[PDB]
Image (cartoon, helix red, strand yellow):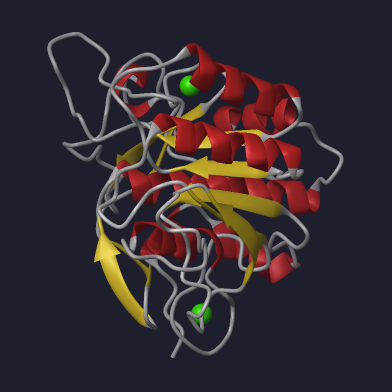
Length: 275
Ligand SMILES: [Ca+2]
Ligand SMILES: [Ca+2]
């Protein structure tokens, strides 16, 4: 029994699936706590680990990386769920440990491994409250090298009239993603600010969990992978397009929801975006 998560339908991915665009050959690096490659519903092409104590990227001792990955590429078969890009080449770049945290050096190292290894799209469902020249260095270089870089905007909510979008999501070169529910309302925890680009489903997102399980989670970490997936579908239909063009498309065919400070350019529509 294969269940199609609401979010995958909400961003109109199945329309592209029916046409034959499912992300084939598009490499997507999931920079997270690793991905359980043994999960029947995910096919992991490769990766690397930068957590000195957890050298196996195919071992997810946290569960977060696996869930994010499921939303990106859960296989289209007879079981579990269905990712936004079920045919994408899933790369596990493990930079976060068992408890969920990592050092910036580990994270940066992973971003750099992805650039070095020709990733097409990088997904970062993580953010820090403070930045660094080396972090900005890493993301700016990825984009300059053709990579589409996507990141969760953060779960800080609202604070006066100030931005709560964390890094690397804050940098202009990075696609900052907010979380909306099934009724398109902004999640109360979703970070706000002028750096917000788009919104995607982020509440009660059903996905893959370590040890052949499935569970729902809420957070902008669940939102970012939908847009990361969206990029893969667009790239599968238009392999010749640059990351700039892909981004433009995602941002210019959205469904406006409210003020950009809280919803960015709005909810993404991959059917419109893929042209
Ligand atoms: Ca499945
Ligand atoms: Ca940004």
